[PDB]
Length: 284
Length: 285
Image 1 (cartoon, each protein chain N blue to C red):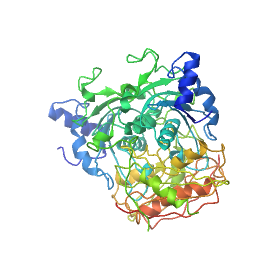
Image 2 (image 1 turned 180 degrees about the horizontal axis):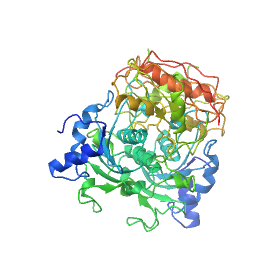
Image 3 (image 1 turned 135 degrees about the vertical axis):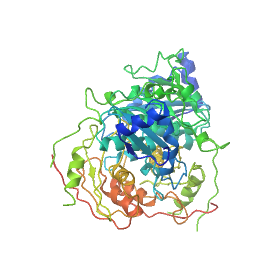
Image 4 (image 1 turned 135 degrees about the horizontal axis):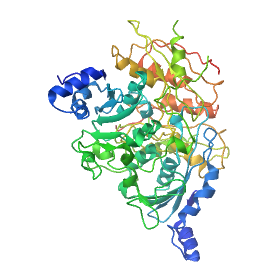
């Protein structure tokens, strides 16, 4: 019962599996890391990184790194970012623990700062070559809180004063293949630059997907709207990259500050030639 | 205000004040913030660093108001590009206006002995100082800023760093524009994906520029080839015109692994309508 795990594991199925092994639900995380590495679509690096996290609801979420060949590296999505997107799409309110296959890069540790109480997030690293589990401030299970991984951070408070996180009910008000990409943009997260984005995708078997746009205090570690929609295809989907068809809406103000129009098409046309146009017209 | 202060001019200024060059660094952070082209954030971040040669380098963050945020270049990355173009071998100290993001702390891991780099933060609201591992001057080594890192050693074994003399061999298939972009790709740093890149730029008065490609163990914190040439414009330039004329680039022979061709033009055509073609010609792969 340790092969081919689901990308989202229900609370009843998780605590039961831990009870038969005699371990805790927290202690079950590193046992789910190794099999999840097979899901890694890494054409470039051939380096499989998986991360399995636990929320406050009790549900177990999975995160996996994906890469895009023939594109610049900043189009690639790390495992840590995948986990955040995965639980956000399922409406998970909190993230407390996660076991990762390898030491999280600074790019991801900076990205995690968008979550409330981010430094309190305990982290365990599976990589035997890494020795974070043996730190002087480590847990009794080897977990180490994110605050120790990224001390003296550059958080959202450095640009804003008293704001809402990304995992909360981000629902800004603004106004059928395109009708689904509207509700995706409503759940976007861009408090630094006021440019939300929502991306929906269809399948050859008629599966509806979604993606939005979540910003970080540091600009570069931003999760692309298209990229956040491709995670809804690999997980809970068929698993195909040259089978993308539909495009989606971009809520720019006359293409104001953060244009993702041309970058979306450039990305899709390289991974799937049979792409469609986009509509960059939305207000409020 | 100058982007590069010579060792003879730096050590002299410190000798006349009777102080050390190290304690002289944080005074240059504040005025350097004015160079920040930040149309989006309106948040000026400057960083002044000191190398092993004794020369003082400056780093400043730049933003692009018509591109996605992952095209923007932070102050720390600017500093790295700046000293590599001047052939600085090592980086020991730098005082930064604000707490360096994880994106930059991960990017700095490409330098040999990166964790030993002591860091001072000017921002009084930040509490990097008084750390359990803080210096007697308030400096904190980068290793404490990004502990238990994901370094190059996780993907490589016994290799050359980023600050060393990286010299990969590549040949080809406005005559002094492609000849300069050839030697630029030769000084590139891409040991993870074997795709070097060199970008040259011209001026209205005919000034030849250059830009590397420096890769990171983590993919996203990658320094773009065009961006690393754009830092050669902000520094050692007029300060600053986005109305210049493209230009050059050297990518792989028929787009091997990491194609940046179409993305390069996409960046340039938005900031400067007067763009040029690209050269996908490199050998000895």
